[PDB]
Image (cartoon, coloured by chain):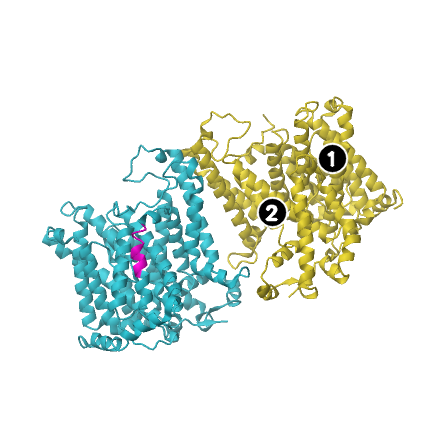
Chain colours: A cyan, B yellow
Amino acid sequence: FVPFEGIKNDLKGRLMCYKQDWTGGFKAGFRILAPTTYIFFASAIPVISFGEQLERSTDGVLTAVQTLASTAICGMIHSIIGGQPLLILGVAEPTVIMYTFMFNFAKARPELGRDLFLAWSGWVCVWTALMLFVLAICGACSIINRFTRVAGELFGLLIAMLFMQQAIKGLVDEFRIPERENQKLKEFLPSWRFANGMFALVLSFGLLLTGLRSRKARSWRYGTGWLRSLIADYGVPLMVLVWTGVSYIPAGDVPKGIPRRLFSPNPWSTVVKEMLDVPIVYIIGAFIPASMIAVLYYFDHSVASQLAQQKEFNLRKPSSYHYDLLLLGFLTLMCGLLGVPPSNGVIPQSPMHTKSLAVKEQRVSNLLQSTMVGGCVAAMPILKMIPTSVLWGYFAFMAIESLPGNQFWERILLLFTAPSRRFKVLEDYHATFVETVPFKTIAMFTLFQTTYLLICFGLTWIPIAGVMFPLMIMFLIPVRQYLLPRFFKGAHLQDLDAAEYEEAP
Amino acid sequence: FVPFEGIKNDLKGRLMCYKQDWTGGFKAGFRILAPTTYIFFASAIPVISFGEQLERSTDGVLTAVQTLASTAICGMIHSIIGGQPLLILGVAEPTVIMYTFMFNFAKARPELGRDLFLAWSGWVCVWTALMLFVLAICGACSIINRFTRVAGELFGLLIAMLFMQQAIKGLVDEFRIPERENQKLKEFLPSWRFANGMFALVLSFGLLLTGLRSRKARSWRYGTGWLRSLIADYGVPLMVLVWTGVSYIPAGDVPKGIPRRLFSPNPWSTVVKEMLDVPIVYIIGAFIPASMIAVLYYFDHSVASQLAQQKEFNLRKPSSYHYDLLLLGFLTLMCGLLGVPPSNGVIPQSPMHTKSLAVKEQRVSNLLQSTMVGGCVAAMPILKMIPTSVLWGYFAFMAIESLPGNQFWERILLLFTAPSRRFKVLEDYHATFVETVPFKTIAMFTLFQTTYLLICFGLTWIPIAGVMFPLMIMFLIPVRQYLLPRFFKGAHLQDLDAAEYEEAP
């Protein structure tokens, strides 16, 4: 834990291959475009969805433009001067939730109001940058091995529940009048509103089901190999385009806002000044949410890097955890100054990128994908054709796609499985702890984990205290270290909380 | 082919067990209700759907009331005095198509008009009864072994295509104004019409997907055994009820006819006289459609009986093909006199009934199920709560459910399968001809069968000549006998057109 030792080691290790990182990427030629576009499509659409969420939750202060710009700039900077280019940066849901809490707090306080929300966010980002600098200097990344499976799967499931909640919220609001829209327009009559709601339901469910089916196209029997691969890789964008076109079918026989489309404005049509006007008391109070955003980033960046640098990939280059965290602090400071939400490592974008590069490790794919994500801002008129129902369907799609490889979800299903029926579980691929651990212990572990998850999810509903859930997430580390061994017996915990995904036939 | 020999033999064989047929049913006790209700639910809903189809195609002359009454009465009469009680009688789609053609013909001719449509149908039914009497007396049922697989699967696929066409027609018409409804009502405004259309889409697709998923509930892992069996048996009615309730959710915030519901009237709120007023020329011309209805019935009754009396069931009682055909002629005459469409054997209602009775062969289950089908007429107000979108979804459901066990559909899929990909077909359960027959011969056979099917389907679109498709169906017998052996080599035809469903692991 010697200060500056880790950063120096990572810089030394990554400074002997920089020219190699660039040359190998240039040597790959035009063949490097396929992974680049794959990751770009995996990254942009969730960013646009988070931007629409922020727009509906921030009264239009933040939109898809800000999220796209932040993602793009942070990605280019990380690719050029970052330590681990395989890591993919972008705006994530927890950041959206934090900013929603901060906006709700600011709106209710006249001293700040909606006008100083971005300035208060910038001060929060300054504080977060300071804490990340401290954590990176003190070598707190040397203990990332304690972010065991339990916390990772609990956080993943919580994010999935938030995604589903947002999808349901959007589908419900499709039946209502927007808060900041003219109420006299024809499209907002009760009949047209009901029609828009049902059309949104149709489009969202179609998108969801078609994408889920397409995710397993390479396993299909029909079609050519290249077509099957193209589908399995780009079903989400392809289905988005298809259902947009479907939405455009009755365009001639209905009003203009039927179905509703992206509310994000077209930009074609710095806040350091206001950060000086914020009262000192609120500048100090920004310490609170900054600590929790810093905790979230310290967790997510490290976990995403660990996933992207799995030993099975046979990577021949070292890791840059500490320098990556320091650069994340710098990026957070810069984004707060610019008036955009900060970006951090995302999952499974980084492992998917590494798999697509399987390894051809270089800094060109990330740079290019961030460049096109930023250029999508210039294509805002085209993106504005996408209905919001498709975005809600995509939210539900991610919520459902967070489940497959999650052991907590499988253990919940086992808990809800009938006693006379577990042979069916044993008839297919299953985890080792099913055989090597008694069912009662698995049930107790799953019940404790589910209670913790539901407590965190309920806390998220509290107006002000709901900004504390990262603290609960981080409390799982010492709990797993100290308390669980008291109530559990060694190998049971090791199998139920193994750092490796163990499967049996 | 000695006249009256077959009928005498069947009557003799079935007259030594009649008292046994009744006593065994009475001895079963209340346990006989489960198969009874299962078959009643399998029979009623398609009958209601066909009634709605006739209502929309007959300008309200025929509705679900007539179809239900015909099904009920014919079923009770067959159970009491029929030869094969396991056979289930009801109104089928080909009868609906024939009556639609006859109504379209009558409407365009002023001498008949809509007022004499039922009288002309009664004369057609009299002719059909005479032809069925002739066929049963001449022993034409001694050659039912020539109704090979090719014709059966072609007819099944044609009926499936008709079902899907009707479902699409209904879903499209949900977006429009009914022909015989007040156009000034609020529910028929463009906005409300669009809303009703999209709600219909939602309900129909939900019903379809949920029913398809529920059909394999016994294979699920979740839930109790009794619950899984109940779902796998009654998913269709359960899903109908669920989606009706869903349709009732926004009832308070929308107009009265949103969503649209059954147009069949509530009866609570004989045509021999008019058959004398029909011109003699049309009485003679009724010979034409009568012959084809007779051909359809001679095919379907015999095939359904053969399926319900499969040797695997180990039935200890003889068959009554000829007497069954004679009784069908009598029932057709009676129904034509009463002014209702005739009923005939249906598939897979009879095999499903036999399976549910697996065999406890008796006349009580059919009698009871027909009695409750008839009593459903008294429950017309309750049935009128069901939206039409659910019925269109059920149409699509039957269309899709006609495919699984059909070898023609599998061979079409194989034809559209990629050459480098047939190992995937070989990786699962498959038919024997896949291994024992070259692919080129299978492709030629499938192409010929598909061309024949498409020709029949296109003929069905002709206004007047579309009533000739049963003749094409019957032409497959002599074709298979004489022409195919010229172009095919023995064992190839035997495997591709085997009377037994041969499967390989």
Q: Secondary structure at mark 1?
A: helix
Q: Say yes or no: labels 1 and 2 on the same chain.
A: yes
Q: CA distance from mark 1 to mark 2?
A: 26 Å
Q: Position of residue B463 (x, y in %)?
A: 66, 35
Name which quarter of the figure residue B106 lies in.
Answer: top right
> In the drawing, does residue B395 fall left or right of residue A432?
right
Front tag of 1 and 2: 1
Q: Position of residue A437 (x, y in %)?
A: 44, 71
Q: Which range of residues does the magenta coloring cover?
A: A370-379
Say which chain tag 2 marks. Answer: B
- Which numbered circle lies on residue A473? none
Q: Position of residue A464 (x, y in %)?
A: 23, 52
Kind of residue at disc 1: Pro
Kind of residue at disc 2: Ala
Residue ID for mark 2:
B399
- Which numbered circle lies on residue B289? 1
